[PDB]
Image (cartoon, rainbow over all chains, first blue to last red):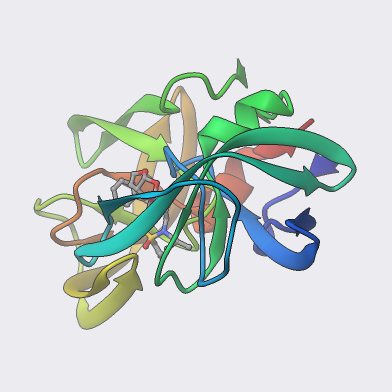
Length: 99
Length: 99
Ligand SMILES: CC(C)CN(C[C@@H](O)[C@H](Cc1ccccc1)NC(=O)O[C@H]1CO[C@H]2OCC[C@H]21)S(=O)(=O)c1ccc(N)cc1
């Protein structure tokens, strides 16, 4: 799928049996979701962005099915206004920027 | 160009005769730059992101030469960790996400 940028690049994803919409974000190193539970042992970390830094929980090898592809990787959970698919997962679907 | 996401998608830009590197951020609605001088008036505004909000200056009709393409539009100036090229200018260079 080719995606233009006239609107927010939101895709439907399935993570841990839950349906969500997440932002394909080339400016995010990492993937972060709002509150939810996930398998495995998590380490507490802190991520930073435009407005400051937030405390989040980091999970490794989480499965996300994004628009029909499958990816496994670190998924961080914490207070974000959007669900964001950082580059860690974008690489795994072979997502590129073109112009 | 085609840009993979294994590394941060930075490009060199020329804005107001200054050479800068900026992020091709599909998660950003607008464009924000570090502290600098610019032409025209500016209304003070506030942008929100991961971790809160910041006060910034908003300029209109600002020209940027991105990787040899020219675009004009609203550029925000304020305390960001990265210069960010948002959708408000990515659409003008015809930039798309592909996978
Ligand atoms: C909150 C997002 C939906 C939108 N953001 C763009 C996003 O790409 C930022 C852009 C960004 C890039 C570097 C530093 C701060 C913000 N990246 C980000 O927050 O990512 C964090 C999680 O992954 C890590 O990667 C780096 C920061 C971490 S934003 O910075 O807050 C933003 C929102 C609106 C505008 N007009 C401009 C910028």
